[PDB]
Image (cartoon, rainbow, N blue to C red; front, side, top):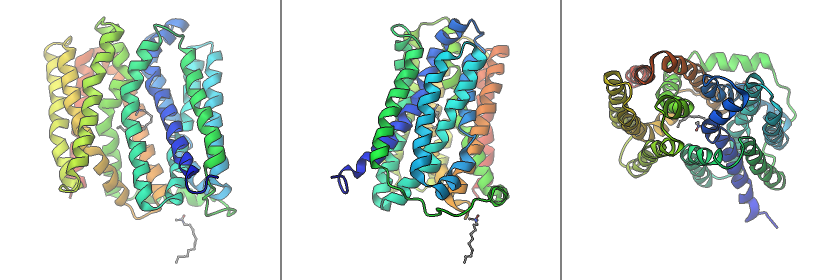
Length: 392
Ligand SMILES: CCCCCCCCCCCC[N+](C)(C)[O-]
Ligand SMILES: CCCCCCCCCCCC[N+](C)(C)[O-]
């Protein structure tokens, strides 16, 4: 009757919801070619779909943690899942690529609920031991989605309409809702205390005064930008630009995200014998080399996408190795409340992702693949520059 055993339905449905929102990005990108063809809109709106999605995900970030603390985790979390379901369904009525993009933004708001409320309840619900396993599963979900999403999405548009994908996301989120409704406990400490936006603002201005934290948080954004820009732009780079098929598009995803996974796997084996600082340095080598290779190759020949793919694969391996550690060090760089620290670094990342994808898009539209990879290289260099400051 659920006390001990079915308690695990709560983290399981949170994980399911997380997955739904992630493929809500990752399946959609390859489907954006069908979408933009349906609306008769330019291919410049393809990466923008992801920009809007991620922009929405920085929207309520700062708010939801302290808000749910006051009015409770259950009603806020469940409202987020419902909002995801409703906005997933509403996009079928879009009628315009501008209105489509607006709904991508509104959909992305659902992202904020995962970390700021759902995971806050996890940390408040479970022992440090079990909590570790849960974050591990959430981390693995974040690994699987970008691998499976583009493959499933590319296959999907040869069979079913793009609208069906949003019906899928909504269905999966519906399952999480009913699971969370009957499982998730109320962990909120600060009911019914008042919330000061004035003092909340003061907290964020305080975390932003810490220079090491800001360096680490910005670096996490810059270093992952090439990966996310590839996710955003790969449908137009491959299919539109190189005139390859959907099958090849799918194939190129395998070494890149397989390498990401390989890097995390090597991380799990090294972590007991290696400090996070040295794993950052260890990952730094394939990160810089991979980005250098993709840039140099496509400046020599704009059309070599296999060298670009290899370079991104080597880079993604380094990311897999270096990233989890930088997240930890960045978290611990500030002594403030972890909810405030987490939301701050999530917002700084999203800021770099959204703006960076847009810059990336105009880079490729004007300069082709060479410029795509050159902009990715400067982002690597920005991460590197921040690391020599960050440590020590
Ligand atoms: C490993 C890169 C870390 C980037 C963190 C992005 C937050 C996830 C928001 C949904 C986006 C899904 N995506 C494209 C990252 O796979
Ligand atoms: C020994 C410390 C206890 C005295 C502080 C009174 C509690 C007020 C809490 C205000 C919240 C501040 N903050 C940083 C969380 O925004």
